[PDB]
Image (cartoon, rainbow, N blue to C red; front, side, top):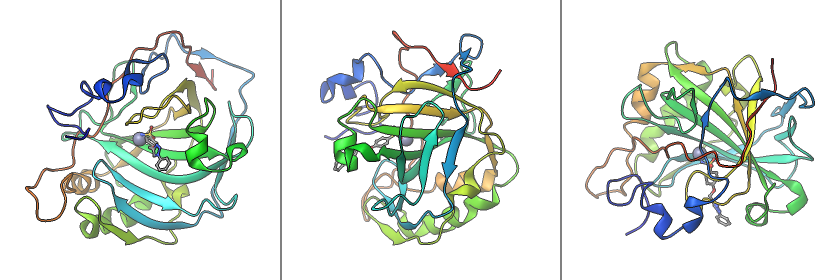
Length: 258
Ligand SMILES: NS(O)(O)c1ccc(OCc2cn(-c3ccccc3)nn2)cc1
Ligand SMILES: [Zn+2]
């Protein structure tokens, strides 16, 4: 009886195995745009993905991860609210069963169809496992998805999904360029938070871009054909793999833009 996104194992149950679920800096949160304050001291984001080396794509039973070679400073995130260098390890998405839900963060209570998380770890801690034990261990760049025009740079991801339909399946996924998933603007909100899945560790500096990317209905429909289950098990569609907004508590969300 492991955690998931069903009625009997979903987000409202997680606290029983992971008491930090009710902690002081949990994610995601609602971003109240009128309360978020412009912070002129915040720097522009530095997203350096030109040397990114993708390796593999994995259905882990709660989403799919596109994994990168993080044994050197290839693809890194710096600047903004961050001190030091954060290495890209993987990206994944959260999405809904319908276009009107799927994102984890919300903006003035608006839910987007999906949310992309580019996960980076602070290289002062040496490896990812050590980094998640630190309050400034990770930086996750969050990007909203809305349904409209297709995102050409997403299609290579979409088309490999039939080969990793079920939990535990992986496929080679080399030479994928994550720059093709970014929006035009790097304007962002930032706040201190947590992993949005168990173990829910409070180790993340969240950087959530204001500008959503557009993906087509056909693209998101292919996300929704994935399975939570393993091969040969009763089919349960991988949809609604998002945690709802958590209490903001003693936190301020800062904006990089006026
Ligand atoms: N959704 S999110 O972007 O917040 C997000 C990002 C990263 C996550 O990592 C889970 C994880 C894996 N490990 C681990 C550590 C050492 C060895 C093996 C696994 N620890 N936490 C979860 C959610
Ligand atoms: Zn995530």
